[PDB]
Image: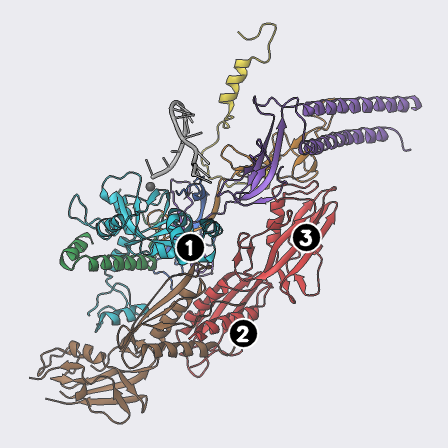
Chain colours: A blue, B purple, C yellow, D cyan, E green, F orange, G red, H brown
Amino acid sequence: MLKLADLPESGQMRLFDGRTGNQFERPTTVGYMYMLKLNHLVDDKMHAR
Amino acid sequence: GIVYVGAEVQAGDILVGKVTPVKDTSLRVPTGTKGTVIDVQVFTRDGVERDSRALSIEKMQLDQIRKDLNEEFRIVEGATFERLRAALVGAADDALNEQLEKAQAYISDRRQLLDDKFEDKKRKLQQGDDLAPGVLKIVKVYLAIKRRIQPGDKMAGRHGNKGVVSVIMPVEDMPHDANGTPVDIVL
Amino acid sequence: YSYTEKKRIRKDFSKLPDVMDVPYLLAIQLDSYREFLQAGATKEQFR
Amino acid sequence: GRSVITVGPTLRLHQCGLPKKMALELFKPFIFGKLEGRGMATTIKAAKKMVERELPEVWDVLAEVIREHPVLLNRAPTLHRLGIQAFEPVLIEGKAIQLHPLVCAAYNADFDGDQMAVHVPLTLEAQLEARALMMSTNNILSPANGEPIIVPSQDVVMGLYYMTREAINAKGEGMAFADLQEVDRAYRSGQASLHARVKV
Amino acid sequence: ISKLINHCYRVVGLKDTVIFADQLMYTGFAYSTISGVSIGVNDFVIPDEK
Amino acid sequence: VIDSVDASRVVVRVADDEVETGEAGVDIYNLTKYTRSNQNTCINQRPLVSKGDVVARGDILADGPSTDMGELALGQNMRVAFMPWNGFNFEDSICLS
Amino acid sequence: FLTPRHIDVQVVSQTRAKITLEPLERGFGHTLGNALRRILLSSMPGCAVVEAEIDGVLHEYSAIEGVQEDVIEILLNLKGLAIKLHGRDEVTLTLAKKGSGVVTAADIQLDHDVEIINGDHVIANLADNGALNMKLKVARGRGYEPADARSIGRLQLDASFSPVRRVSYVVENARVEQRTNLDKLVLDLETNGTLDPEEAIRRAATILQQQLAAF
Amino acid sequence: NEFLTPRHIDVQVVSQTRAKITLEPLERGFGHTLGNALRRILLSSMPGCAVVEAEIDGVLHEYSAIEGVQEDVIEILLNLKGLAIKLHGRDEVTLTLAKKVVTAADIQLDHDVEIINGDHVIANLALNMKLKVARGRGYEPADARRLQLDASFSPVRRVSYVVENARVEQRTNLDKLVLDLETNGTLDPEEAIRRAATILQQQLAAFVD
RNA sequence: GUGGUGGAGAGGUA
Ligand SMILES: [Mg+2]
């Protein structure tokens, strides 16, 4: 599917640093991951007396 | 004595107008709580008066119920009327009159059904509540909070990979692809 | 072919054939209470 | 007080991050004392008025009292004296407690949602006890064994190990350098591989 | 790294030891960020003899 | 078939086959708007059907919280990268754009 | 010590475009490319909708009879509008419509100095009884302005004035026939189409020049 | 619109040639921009003069074994790498050293060339040196085009930078810029920063207005 | 010259 998607086969690409602009020497794994946010927000955790 | 619905409320703002002897038992939003009030509810014990807020609330509720049932009557009555007009030729003699009379009878039956249902719902609404003893009238309010994700909030994927968001750095600092596409999350 | 699936179709990577559909999940609770209630009573309701 | 942790990699070992609101809540009597002293507070009602509205003035005095006041930190399961340590707080905008990554090993505290309890010492005696005996810098070696406990953890170890490798055939191998600064200049220029056999 | 830190503490001192620790963390973080080290499915290598 | 749809209510013209003699088209679904869950989270339902759309029995007319037109959608999916970044993802923390 | 003249811009679409700087010193292009990328992604002045008032609504946690969507979707769609301010910074807009249909940016009233890029941007869908009349005040800002940093019934919105969406760049050599030791910079810029890529480059150049002039 | 435009740059002189500069008020994003840009500027493109060629009399090859001096040829070339020379006369010169202790002052010179430190040591007797010095832009190894040797025409021996939070009472999250410099001594580090700034400015003066 | 929380049960976090 990846090679059908015209994406790099190994699922890894060399990225570019967003501050130095220098490409990282080793290709890194990127992609789309289903990320959740749990009911543990700090707004109800920050107590102070 | 009640906040207008749809009012942004900072911390400590008074919400309910309550009077003691003659001090004030007025309710205030707790500190650290700030949002928008979206709904107010008021309930009164049997034998106690209904405040203008409750009167108005019951007003739009009754209006909504009436309009819903009127529309439900409208759709079915239109279907029946057009079905009858289609059965009859372009505008025998006894059959058409019989069908028109039967349609009128069905329309009257549905009208009386819907009206009786409306009176039943109305009567159900006008009743008081079985509030707790010592409680004359009770009032509750709701608030809406838009919790933006901020550093410290716990985030976890699907494979048992938890995490606490450390910082939120600007878009430039994110690692970007040669095409210029930056990533959002750096695990 | 259902209408809801017609709006978006997931490419299923299942190699195995589906031999029977997943049963209704909440039937475990729902059957118990409704059997305890015996709402529909015959001339002799279920003993 | 308490809150969740957050890794602060820009933190020196002796210092730790601190949310603004926790700082102003905890040190409130100190704020009152300073405000009455310098003169923008005459009555305490006015002092409460400014602290509740948070004028830009209150941040100055808040930073001043925080400046040299050590703060006391501990995790929930404290299994040894390193489980509770003193730090020199740094004000940050947020609700999480920034923590020094090296100290997490002592606390055995990962950032998977751990909450970290904070305390402040009041007496000069207590602050001196914190700074001279409980400061994170003071306790480096484990009391169980002389082995250090403020040790590079996963990521910094990875970086160090990656730096200290050798590639058999890498750009710039075999050429020499007069000084370390020359090596840095060559590498940052990108004309020299990070790990190539060289003379210096 | 642990041995080097322990050795430096007993040799150079404590203030310089913590300075070294902070600098070493800074360098390790920086050059780990420079390194494109990442985990992909191709990294796990199954020997053909298995 | 959907007679009309609004953000709060949905009316369905019931099929003549699956209807009694009288009261033929009656399927009112009042969508539950923003309501409080037991964990103080919002609960609301969204229409996912237009006027005149034919629906079969058991189709999903409107979906509630954490649902994306009939599917279960708990969180969100974003472009992620797996690399140590300035030690901000030091132990398990997350660096956020 | 060559420096680029007569900045060349070519257009892919009314949003996507390419910027090239022919004469550059060797190795210097990557530096400028990163600098321009960061500044462009950081601070371009843009105008986005910050306020929205609908006559029949009180708070955006409600729904309107005849309106296919709740208020929050309306304002979210309204957040994706690409508009331009030619004259003054702050302007107020109006959208009113009654009966069935789909409301786009076309339904908004235009103005002398005010103009909208994405007229095809759907905002909401209306039923037969559907009728909305919404009051919009927009402003031209620079960075992401949340509602918190910014009479009931007036609804605040979070503002992200940045008109740029993605920036990419690459460098190649420039055979100027004088020396092949030169290099040429290709800047791939894709925005919301509201601002001229040449204008963006000139603004970024001025900002960077001022930041350096701090020396 | 308007941004943070600092003026209070400060040079804490940690050494005559090693310096420290800071920039307190700055908008959150430009810290990394300016820091990385200036770092690469100082590394890449500062015109300077350095030796690229030498004639080790009696050492036909690089790894020839020489006598009369305790050290070996690699040490000698590492030494003469370190000299900082400003050439006011030309962009090309070949200098001669002949003596039979070696110091940089032992090299003859004309009114054109100038050596920053003739006190720098190279070797010791118990030495006909013909080395060629040229002007250049940055750090260019001889591999990139005794007869040859690496070069660092840039005058800054070492530059590093780091951005930490900048505290403004009502902004409270900004970037402070911190730069350290180490020039070859041929240039004042603060003057070097000025030179780099003028270079970067003269790059885009065509379009700023 | 004055300042306002017991116990049980259940669940959850580290
Ligand atoms: Mg943990």
User: Which amino acid lies under the numbered mark 3 shown in the image of this protein?
Assistant: Lys
**Spot occupied by residue A45 in the image (x, y as percentages of width and height):** 41, 41
Which image quadrant is residue D67 in? bottom left
Which image quadrant is residue B20 in? top right
Mark 2 neighbour density, 10 Å: few (under 14) some (14–19) many (20 or more):
few
Work out whether mark 3 precedes mark 2 in sequence or the reverse, and give the earlier one: 2
State how far apart marks 3 and 2 are (Cα): 41 Å
The residue closer to the viewer here, G20 or H5, is H5
The image quadrant in which ligand 1 is located? top left
Q: Identify the residue at the far top of this view.
A: C44
The residue that label 2 is drawn on is G8
Q: Identify the residue at the far bottom of this view.
A: H111
The residue that label 1 is drawn on is A8
Residue drawn 40% across and 79% down? Answer: G181
Q: Secondary structure at mark 1?
A: loop
Residue drawn 38% across and 52% down? Answer: D33
Which chain does the residue under circle 2 lie in?
G
